[PDB]
Length: 203
Length: 184
Image: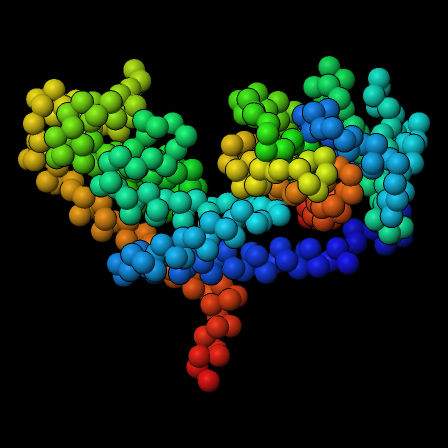
């Protein structure tokens, strides 16, 4: 009964949405160990999928984005086959792949990630790496993100230009990302597994 | 409907174009197993449905009450007429782990073949992630959708795991694209 293999796809679609929603909650509340366990469950479930749609792919991208942000300050961790990419540069690529739902907020989060990707290098004393990151993000004779001229100056004058990074800090990036996660929590809070699970708890 | 006493404009069964690296790089042939087997009733196509220099394809069915036609292509002027008459596309990918891809070309190949200049964009695209047989190491379907940037193409899509020897997954995939057809 190949219908079974099709019933496994449905149950799998449900588990995926449930793990995402649970990962988003651990991110918002600061539960590192819960985040790690839910991450390992999600990793395996993704490996076992037999089919895929654009909706499920977007849900996967959201989980990936959060794992990179959580390691934003861990400069030597590597997430991509190319060893030169830092965690924030990896988060930015993923964010470019998630189809926009809230144009304004999406563009704000994007500009803040581009800025911090360099700032975390500057504040640790890695002037050379910041220069490498800058070249990989803005390195292209064309007009994108208008902060290019400012950040180039900051890099030349090899010293943490706190003055600027203060008004577009790590904390300000984290606040905007957590406002996005709330919009995700509200939408997915109505998925099959979560809803059914609540009724049992209410009894 | 708009006509109670007159017959309607004829609707011929759904037709699909099928191409891809999976049609030659696999140790076991997918087309042979499709042909050389049943529950599916493969028959030669009718000469009337001929598409200059290409033919009339192969006919199949799910259960006597569900029929569709497929034009198999092992290369890439004439194909364009196919891209216009066909209702959907089927890309057969090589999902064997030991393989290394040139994700750039594959994307383009699909890109060309599926241009809205030859037809609507509501036409579904089915990607078959195929391997020779059940004991071969396979690359997960998520990785495939990601490396092929399927969203840039603008066509609704689906990736389904398939096995050339037993045809596992083939049915569930066909069944899906037959609905994006009744959605038209």
